[PDB]
Amino acid sequence: ANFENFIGATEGFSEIAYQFTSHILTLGYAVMLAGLLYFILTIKNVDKKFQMSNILSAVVMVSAFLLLYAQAQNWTSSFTFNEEVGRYFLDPSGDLFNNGYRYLNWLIDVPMLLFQILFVVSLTTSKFSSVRNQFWFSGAMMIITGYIGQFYEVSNLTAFLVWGAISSAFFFHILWVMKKVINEGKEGISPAGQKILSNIWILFLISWTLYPGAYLMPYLTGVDGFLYSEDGVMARQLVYTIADVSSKVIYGVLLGNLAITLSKN
Ligand SMILES: *C\C=C(C)/C=C/C=C(C)/C=C/C1=C(C)CCCC1(C)C
Ligand code: NA
């Protein structure tokens, strides 16, 4: 199956990696619910013209709360403790750990996160529907091909890399079109609003690069090594959670500041 299943069915998890991974994943869905409330309550401090941005943040949190709750209970109900051996092991009766909850929350969210900037800033030379269509297509294909490649994380590894690599090409296209978007969005706004735009670019750049980092994490130190272990599991799932807070919550928080700043023309 995946690589988490491998460790829980050949070596187990110490009670310190199981609970750490259950606490940081629960942190993940709790945040999403505080961002659901924050975005609703803030829908007023922005003009009607930018409110579709906040709405899209509200919906993105509804799908993040629900599905990250799922992934969280998918990890805790997939491993049972062995007092004899003293570690946590894959449970044959449970449903096994399954990434598909996360990856699905990615495919729902990517049009929305990408589409929403185009309600705050104004393009100059590009065409709205041209940018929109390019985002929805490559965003969807990125998450899809990345959902394929990680199926073989344990089996065909050359598949795991080459399919992720394909998912990375769509990712670099998105980065291109976001980059052009940020740029035209700076034309004819204040220096203050331009500073915030610059923030949303460094935030978009780091948060989104984290994801393939988690994808590869157990293989970043060889065929065996430090990470080829429960430690790379602890690490891959802590990185994913920081990426989910950064790209969905801090991203929308920042975009709300810009809208607010642009309310004062
Ligand atoms: C939760 C919201 C968003 C926008 C999530 C984005 C996730 C990625 C950009 C993940 C990308 C991948 C890459 C670059 C290559 C391997 C497969 C991944 C899906 C992990
Ligand atoms: Na996995």
Image (cartoon, rainbow, N blue to C red):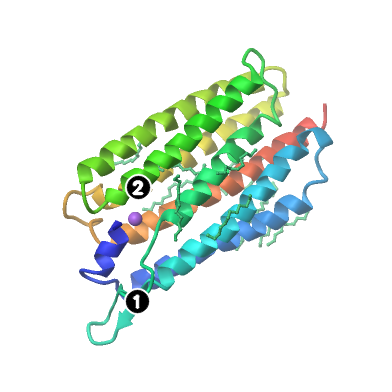
Name the residue at 77% across, 39% down: 51
Q: Note whether residue 3 is visible.
A: yes
Seen from the viewer's position, the closer of residues 205 and 190 is 205
For the residue pair 44 and 56, the one nearer the viewer reads as 56
Nearer to us of marks 1 and 2 is: 1
Q: Position of residue 199 (x, y in %)?
A: 59, 34
Q: Quadrant of residue 253?
A: top right
From what the image shows, is residue 121 above or below residue 43? above
Residue at figure coordinates x 49%, y 35% from the top left: 139
Q: Which residue type does callout 1 highlight?
A: Ser
In the depicted structure, whether residue 50 falls above or below residue 147 = above
Per the image, the residue denoted by label 2 is 215
- Outermost residue, bottom side: 84
Name the residue at the top extreme: 125
- At x 32% / y 35%, what residue is drawn? 165
Q: Residue 72 placed where, x, y %?
A: 48, 65
Where residue 163 sits in the image (x, y, percent)? 31, 38
Q: Nearer the viewer, residue 62 or 215?
A: 62
